[PDB]
Image: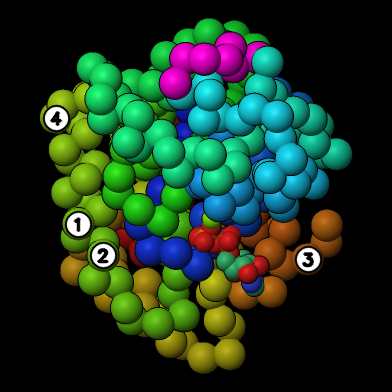
Amino acid sequence: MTRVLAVANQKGGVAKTTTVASIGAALTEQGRRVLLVDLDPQGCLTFSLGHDPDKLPVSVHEVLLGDVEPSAALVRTDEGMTLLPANIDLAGAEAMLLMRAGREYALKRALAKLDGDFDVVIIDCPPSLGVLTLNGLTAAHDVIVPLQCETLAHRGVGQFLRTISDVQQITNPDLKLLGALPTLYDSRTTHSRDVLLDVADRYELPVLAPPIPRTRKSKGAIAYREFADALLRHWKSGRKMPTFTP
Ligand SMILES: Nc1ncnc2c1ncn2[C@@H]1O[C@H](COP(=O)(O)OP(=O)(O)O)[C@@H](O)[C@H]1O
Ligand SMILES: [Mg+2]
């Protein structure tokens, strides 16, 4: 049973890409066959895993258009994860997909061609609420929102939840919002805690545990492995994701 996890937040700089790669690595160490999908035309995930996006002969762009089979675009990573990479060509997807029926299902259609090949698919969405993020949410079974807790600035959470609700109404009724993964947690003061409590109070959004601290045997890596183990057990036995605050 392939599990597809979308990692989404229209706010940039909240450690989405780091989260995708780090959860991917932790799951791989636990024996899962992991595919990572880069849906950001800027190619941050792709670059971070050792591939120059500008030099890829093809990418997820051609895969979303149906011009290249998904298997043909996959590349390898040093840690064993498989990558469906991105480059700047993907910025053109919007103009080209808008002209076609079912633009929201392009990634879903692509992953269907790979089903059974991976235990876990993790999708790194760009910092936007356009067709690429919609493709990520439409293809996923679960979604988490990496959520910075350095500052109280969270005015985008409301529109993000509206987007989840719209997807559930129209393109993906089975999408489950697992919750927010706190990122950039600062242990120096109680401020990050207070930020998370304010978010938990104001928004219909579970705040998950543990927080990822601002940074193999590092505290950030330990927190990612702890969160990845929580994901595993949720998918294995239906255990509810532990929460930062009830
Ligand atoms: N735990 C952390 N501690 C310190 N810096 C981090 C941490 N996680 C991510 N960063 C940095 O934050 C910046 C944005 O991270 P990134 O994963 O690219 O976020 P996003 O994908 O949401 O834009 C990057 O420079 C990254 O190196
Ligand atoms: Mg990113």
Looking at the image, do the residues carrying marks 3 and 4 touch, with CB atoms under 8 Å apart?
no
Q: Position of residue 140 (x, y in %)?
A: 40, 29
Specify the segment rendered in magenta. Answer: 65-71
Q: Amino acid at mark 2?
A: Gly
Tag 2's secondary structure? loop
Residue of label 3: 218
Magenta stretch holds residue 70:
yes
Asked whether the residues under the numbered discs 1 and 2 touch, taking CB atoms below 8 Å apart as contact, a structural biologist would say: yes
* Disc 4 crowd, CA 10 A, few/some/many (<14, 14-19, 20+): few
According to the picture, the residue beneath numbered tag 2 turns out to be 156
Name which residue lies at 14% across and 30% down. Answer: 169
Question: Which of the two discs, 3 and 2, sits closer to the camera?
Answer: 2
The mark nearer the N terminus, 1 or 3, is 1
Image quarter of the C terminus = bottom left
For disc 1, the neighbor class at 10 Å (few under 14, some 14 to 19, many from 20) is few
CA separation in Å, label 1 and label 3:
34 Å
Q: Is residue 167 above or below residue 161?
A: above
User: What is the spatial separation of the Cα atoms under label 3 and label 2, in whole angstroms?
Assistant: 30 Å
Return the residue at label 4.
Answer: 169
- Label 4 is placed on what type of residue? Gln
The secondary structure type at the circle numbered 4 is helix
Q: Residue 238 location in percent, x, y?
A: 44, 28
Q: Residue at x 16, y 26 (%)?
A: 170
| Frontmost residue, 146 versus 45 | 45
Residue 109 seen in this snapshot: yes
